[PDB]
Image: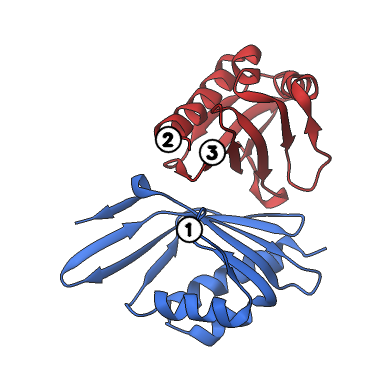
Chain colours: A red, B blue
Amino acid sequence: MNTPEHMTAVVQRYVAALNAGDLDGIVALFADDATVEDPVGSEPRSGTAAIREGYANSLKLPLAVELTQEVRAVANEAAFAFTVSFEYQGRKTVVAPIDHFRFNGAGKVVSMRALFGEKNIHAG
Amino acid sequence: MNTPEHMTAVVQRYVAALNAGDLDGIVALFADDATVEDPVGSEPRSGTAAIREGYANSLKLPLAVELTQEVRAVANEAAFAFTVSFEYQGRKTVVAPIDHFRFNGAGKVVSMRALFGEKNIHAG
């Protein structure tokens, strides 16, 4: 089983590499066969290649990310509240999702899912 | 598809019903083939009576339950950050979970999963 300590560190490392625009940093956290469904309802991004590629796009503007509450972690899974802030064409946006990782035996994230809807997308 | 509003209202009712010790009200929100895994990693409670028994065991003590953040809802799923507090023999506990609902076509909750661990709990 994974330790809550380890899952909580991965979540903190994820947030910090997004802030640093550290693509490798983000890719290394996932299993080779990991899936990402971000947002929930959208077509899943499968395998290292697709996931990196997704993250590059999401890194095309500068992001400011913050965990807005304690990480929750138990049984190989973790969830966390946070925000991602960015600016485009003079318009500031703040997205507030809840994300959920599942972790495999090796401590890598095999599944990521991002739940947030239009009502969790705010102005600056 | 469910609307985000319907699911956000369901979360709101779920929370009001826990506060009011309204057992019938909680169970009504559920599909009668619904499952409930509280906490993530325990064996699920499957179907209405099992589920009803779960909630009657929760309501053995009075609960104070409050949302601590905006609800997240998109494509038939919702997730929410909240605290549940109770007191037993002068001793106060505070659990800070993140729950996740999936819904069916009829607007009913088909699964709840409550993700928290010992780091999300304070007894004192």
Distance from the alpha carbon under mark 3 to that under mark 2: 22 Å
One can see residue B98 in this view: yes
> Nearest the camera: A66 or B17?
B17
Tag 1–tag 2 contact (CB < 8 Å): no
Q: Position of residue B116 (x, y in %)?
A: 44, 51
- Label count reads 3
Mark 1 is surrounded, within 10 Å at the Cα level, by few (under 14), some (14 to 19) or many (20 or more) other residues, namely: some
In this picture, residue B91 sits left or right of residue B75: left
Residue position for label 3? A82
SS for callout 1: loop
Chain holding disc 1 = B
Q: Is residue A81 above or below residue A21?
A: below
Mark 3 is surrounded, within 10 Å at the Cα level, by few (under 14), some (14 to 19) or many (20 or more) other residues, namely: some
One can see residue A96 in this view: no
The part of the image, by quadrant, that contains residue B62 is: bottom left
In this picture, residue B56 sits left or right of residue A56: left
Distance from the alpha carbon under mark 1 to that under mark 2: 16 Å
> Same chain, marks 3 and 2?
yes
Q: Amino acid at mark 3?
A: Phe
SS for callout 3: strand
| Residue at 58%, 80% in the rendered image | B27
The part of the image, by quadrant, that contains residue A58 is: top right
| Residue at 49%, 80% in the rendered image | B53
Residue position for label 2? A3
Q: Residue B39: which disc?
A: 1
In primary-sequence order, the first of circles 3 and 2 is 2
Q: Position of residue B79 (x, y in %)?
A: 60, 55
Q: Residue A17: which disc?
A: none
Q: Position of residue A79 (x, y in %)?
A: 53, 43
Q: Amino acid at mark 1?
A: Pro
Chain holding disc 3 = A
